[PDB]
Every structure is written in C-alpha cells, then in structure tokens.
Image (spheres, coloured by chain):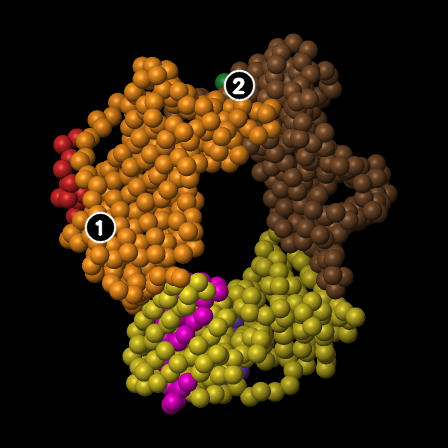
Chain colours: A yellow, B orange, C brown, D red, E green, F purple
Amino acid sequence: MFEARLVQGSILKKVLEALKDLINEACWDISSSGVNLQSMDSSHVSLVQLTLRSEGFDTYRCDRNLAMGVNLTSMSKILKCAGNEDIITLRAEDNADTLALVFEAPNQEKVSDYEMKLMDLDVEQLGIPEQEYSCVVKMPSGEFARICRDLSHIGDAVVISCAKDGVKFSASGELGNGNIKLSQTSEEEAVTIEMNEPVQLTFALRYLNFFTKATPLSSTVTLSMSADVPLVVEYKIADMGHLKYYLAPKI
Amino acid sequence: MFEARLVQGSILKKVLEALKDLINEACWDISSSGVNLQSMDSSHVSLVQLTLRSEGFDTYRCDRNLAMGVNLTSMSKILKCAGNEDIITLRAEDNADTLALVFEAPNQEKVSDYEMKLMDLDVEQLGIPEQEYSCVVKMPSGEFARICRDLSHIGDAVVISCAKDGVKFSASGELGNGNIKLSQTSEEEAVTIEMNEPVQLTFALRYLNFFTKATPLSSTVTLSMSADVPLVVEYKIADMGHLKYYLAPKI
Amino acid sequence: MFEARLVQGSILKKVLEALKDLINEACWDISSSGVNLQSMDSSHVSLVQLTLRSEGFDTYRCDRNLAMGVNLTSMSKILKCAGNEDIITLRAEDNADTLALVFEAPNQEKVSDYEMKLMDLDVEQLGIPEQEYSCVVKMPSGEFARICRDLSHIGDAVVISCAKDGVKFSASGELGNGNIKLSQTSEEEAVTIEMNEPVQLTFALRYLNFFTKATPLSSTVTLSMSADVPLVVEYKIADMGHLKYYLAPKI
Amino acid sequence: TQGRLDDFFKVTG
Amino acid sequence: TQGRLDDFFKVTG
Amino acid sequence: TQGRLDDFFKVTG
C-alpha cells in the first residue's frame, strides 16, 4: 500500500505542469525512499528525471516497490482541481490499477478525492553516466526563462557560448540577430560560472522553453555543458529532490 | 415615469453579467415596490428570478406598473461602458419604447447616457409554489463556484448527495472520477447543512456554471434540494433583494 | 556615429507600442538635436509625429544627420526583449544599414544586444501649418482611452461636439446610441476646455483607438479641433518631447 | 435524461 | 465619408 | 541537425 501526504500541494501541481508539456505519459517508480520518474519525450530529443524523497512528505508509506504507469496530461488536469494551499495525498493499493489523489482544503470543511486509471508502460532503460562538465552556470530561474523567451522571438535555436568573462546566448532570424551575455556577479539572484574550458553548443529553443515551465519550482537553475554532449538543466525542489532535464544539441 | 438611481452601479453590472449567459431576453416588471424579473432559458431547463427592492436605490420613482421587454445581451454590453464606481440611473417614460441608462463617473466631470430600444416579449406565467426542501446547504459562493468548475473538468453532470455528515458532489468522465465532500463547520466562509432526509440528485454542470456567474454578488450561496424537484440556487444581493436560479434535475 | 542612451527604456518600449499598430515602417530622422519621426498610415487617414530631444537621453551623440528607414513591427518585437527597467541604447554607424539596440538589465550581470537591418524608405514631405484651433480639450489620458473604448462598443464613428459647458462624444449603432459629456473641472486628472466657437466633427473610432495606445506615455492628453480640419491628439513624453497624431474627419 | 421545468411546474405563460 | 489628410494638407513627399 | 539522446546515451529500454 502506498500513501504519500504532501502538505505543500502546490509543489506537485508545479511538477505536473513542468512535466505535461514535455511528456504525456511516464512511469512513477515508487519505493520506501521516495518517488523517481524518468522518461524521454517521443522524439528522444530530451529526457526528464524527477526525484521526490520520502523525507519531503508529511506522511510517507510504500510497503513495496511500485512502477505506476501514468497519463501525465490526465494527472495534471486533475491536479488543476487542487487549490494552491491544499494538502495533497497520493494513494494506491499494492497491485494498483488506479491512483487516488486526495486534496484537503485549508478550510477543513472540504475534501476532494479523485481517482484515475493507471496504464501499462514499457519503461525504458537509459544509461546516463553522471560525469563532469566543461562549464556549469548557476543563475536565477526567472532570468533563464526570460532569456529563452526573448531569443525565441528572434530565432528557433540558441547558440550557447562559454568563455572567460561569462556565457552568451545567441539566436538569429528574419528580423535580425541577438545575443544575451551573462557575467559573474560579486544564492537566488546571483550568477556563478565555473568554466573548465570554452564550450559552444547549439540547442532548440522549443525544448528549452518546455524546461522553463519548471521555473516556479526553484529560484535558481543550473546549466551544465560539455562539447558534443547533452545539456543538463536542473531545478532543485527545496528539500524534496530535483527535476533534471537533458537536451541533445543540434548536430 | 420611471427613475431608479443606484449609487453602487457595480451591482447592476454584476446582475446583467449573471443573467446574459443564461438568458438573452427578459421582461423587467417595474412598480413602486421595485424591480422583478423572471424568465426561463430557451430549453426551459432553468429559470432565473431577480428581485431589486426600491429601498435599495438612492432615488426610486415608478408612477405606474411597467413591463419592459429587454435584450439582456445588449443591456450587458452597454453596462460594460459603466465604471465599477459609477452611479447608474435607469430611466423610462410611461409608455416607454426605449430605456435610458445614465452613468455618473466618480470624478463628476464625466456623465454618460445610453439609450437602447425595448422589445415586445410574451412574458410567460410560471407557477412555482414556495415549499420546504429536504436539504438546504449554505456555503461560501466562491467555494461553490470552484466545486462546479473543478468537476466540470471531470464530467458533464454532477451527482449531489446529502446525508448525515455533509454533502457530496460527484462526477465521472473519461479521465477518471471525483467527489468533493463538504462537512458542516463549527456567515460568509462557513458551511451549514440542514437535512430533513437524505437526498440524491443529478444536475448538468453547464447550467450550474452559468449560475456561479452570480458569485460576485454575494459572499454566500444557498442550495435547496428535494427528491424529484428542481434545485434552487440563491444569491442574496445585500439589502437589495436576491437572484434565484432553478434547475430541473436529470431524469 | 550615433549613440543614444535612454535610462528609462520603458519610454522607448511604450513609443514603439504606440506606433506599430498605426504604421509598420517609418524613417527616424536623427541629428544632434534628437530624434524626429513622421509618417502617415497607408490610407493617409492619419499621421503620427514623434519628437525625442537629445536632452532626454543620458548620453546622446549624433555626429551627422541620419534618416534610418525602420520596420516598426520588427523594432517593437525586439523591444519586447527589453525589461521595463532596462537601460536602452540605440547605436548606428555613419552610413548605417543596421541598427543596434543594447539593453542593460538592472542587475548588471545581463546585457543584451540586438541588431536589425535598416530599409530604404521614400520619406514623404507633408506640409502641416501649425495653427490655432477653435477648441482645445485637455483631459486625463486614461479617461480619453476609456471614452473611445466604450463608444467603440456602440458604433464605428464618434461625433465630437464642443460648446459652452463641455464637450460631448456621441456614437450610434444597432444596439442603441450613447453620448459621453465632459464638463470643465474646478494637471493630470482635471479637464480644461478652451472654446473659441462651437465645433462639431465626426471621426472613425478605429483610428482613435490606435492613438490611445500611447496612453501609458502620459497622464494627460490634449485634443485640438476646428471645423473641416484634421483632429490633433497629443501626448507629452515627460521631458523628452511628444507624440502627436492627426486624423482626417469623416466627410 | 435532462428534464425540463415544465415537467415540474405549471407554466401557461 | 472618411476623408484623407491629403484633402487637408499639401504633401508632395 | 537536431540530434537525439540515443546518439549520446545507451538506452535499451
């Protein structure tokens, strides 16, 4: 039997909002340690990895390992029925074919219970060796979102260049070209850039704009890059875990 | 001659907004005691009844009984030209074929006057005997609006069940099923449930979502139900009167 | 070489927003004294004239007179990439075929640079003799915007009548007719009306609603009218210059 | 099936 | 009928 | 051209 009670339900609402636009279905691997979710989008251009530790929940119970196949589009729609101040509980039986979501309003006079069917999903393995990157940039999450949004008005792809001094994001299109340069500042609104060697990569803005849907989950975002390797964009979910996105570069 | 001066014009703006989505035309019966309006929508599935007592207006004059046929869609559009802090005056001559609406801006330098044509309407009688219901629920109007909105994401109909303990609203659809339960609290943000006997009824959410357009008119809403009889949803218009909606159940 | 540094970049953002809806291309005549822009829309029904004095910029340099042909639709899109608190710099070389726009974020860690191509434009002369009008009305810019918006819900044209007592705006349509009357008050939220003789003119609301896109540029707006002559609507850009619109009346 | 208020109230309007 | 500014001003631009 | 993560990672899922 599975029981996960999250007092700050808005966290789950934000997670689904950050997932649904990128992937429509995924397997939520549940265990005594928490919730793990990993899935590539249909085009295999990006991969999302979610971690929600048991310690982050008010109450957490998962007698046995479970792999629940879930329609994220449907789950997000149901989470729309939860207030931002609702306590949210996810509940499932041992051999669950359904997932129950319970929302407790802050007024204590209203309690909602939603049940959605689970689905069989061919959860695919995806060996990704955690390594070190040539360049790691940490910046305000809102700042990164605004950069991706702005350049999207200019082009469909962004060239990210790293070197001594800062990081530059460049795009070009029919209306002209633009470059946004970020230089290290002197935790939330600061910019830190650790460079091992200059790196230049091109990425599709369409996917980056999907990643920034996770902005409300954290005040900061960290970008990790290395030549000819997937970009990694990470958002820490305050004392819960994190949401990591991987994106294959162009070429 | 008819002259009704309402200092808090926003009230009239809200009334028309709450009417126009349900009905497009209606007869405003005017007399020395105030304004009365009653009309069923085209499908005769719902009925709305409005009461605005003369006492609620700054100035009120209605020498004789009048029954003005009005296009509510047009009236609401004209009321959109009134500020939320405007004093609104409705004016009409004895054998009126036109209705004048005067909006006085709070700056006293701007006064607007709109005139719309009236129409011949076959105001239909509709005997509805005021009786007692098996269950009457009083709750925050915003709460009820949110319930109807949420379940609308799940299904097209809502099963309302009443019993000892509370009232439950249930809906089911392709994405799953949901139930919202309300239990009595211990005036504006409280829930009171008076039950004479358990009652279970099914209603179309499309109509309930039309009723909740009246939410801004009152902090509270009262639902009255009895087996095999129309549901009644009422919003009190603070020291003016009320707006009552009736809805035929399914089956 | 041209260099114009505007600390309050929002001003330029607002100017382009006020221009783009009326005209898509225009020549920005630049000189040591500042920026001048004048252009009629394709139908020659209206004309816009912009003045931005050098004194209004933090830094201003323009070694020689320049006439840059610019696609305002494209320029406005690029200005959308500038924050409302960004310092904006416009830069161009002597025989410029491109315009550079630099946006400096208030955090000092982010600097954006956009470059758009310039275009050859047949800047047309348009002799307009500055004269005196029969009636000049000064009122809150938001007030005028609301008047034009409201009457647009009633008709497609507005009859503006001036006489002793005030100014009236009238429109009529299928839903009825309306008139808004403004009477002199006793700087920002006041109404002043100077009348030399009664004047009555008809104008298309579609164009007036384009003019009010300039509302955020000033708290006040001044309307100048005379029989059988174009209407003039002016917005002062606080210690920078102004934005003047001319509109040919109907008939 | 959705009912109509006529099945619940007398009209004659 | 809507007039044009050319009927009110000399252009030659 | 846009690459896919399969060109960078081993899957076999």
**Given the image, what chain letter belongs to the residue carrying mark 2?**
C
| Residue C25: percent from left, percent from top | 63, 39
* Left or right relative to A121: residue C10: right
Residue under the point 24% across and 63% down: B163
Q: In this view, does C121 lie to the left or right of B139?
A: right
Report the residue marked by disc 1.
B133
User: On the picture, is C174 further left or further right than A136?
Assistant: left
Amino acid tagged 1: Tyr
Q: Is mark 2 on a helix, strand or loop?
A: strand
What are the residue bounds of the magenta stretch? A61-90
Task: Bin the neighbour count of mark 1 within 10 Å (Cα to Cα): few under 14, some 14-19, many 20 and up.
Answer: some
Using the image, tell me which numbered label, if any, was put on residue C159. 2
Identified at 76% across, 34% down, the residue is C241
For residue C54, which numbered disc appears in the image?
Answer: none
Q: Identify the residue at image location x=50%, y=71%.
A: A8
Question: Residue A1, percent across and down?
Answer: 35, 85
- Eyeballing the image, is A116 above or below C33? below
Q: What residue type is labelled 2?
A: Val
Q: Is residue B52 visible?
A: yes
Would residue C149 be visible to someone looking at this image? no
Q: In this view, does C232 lie above or below C213?
A: above
Q: Which of A68 and A123 is in front in this view?
A: A68
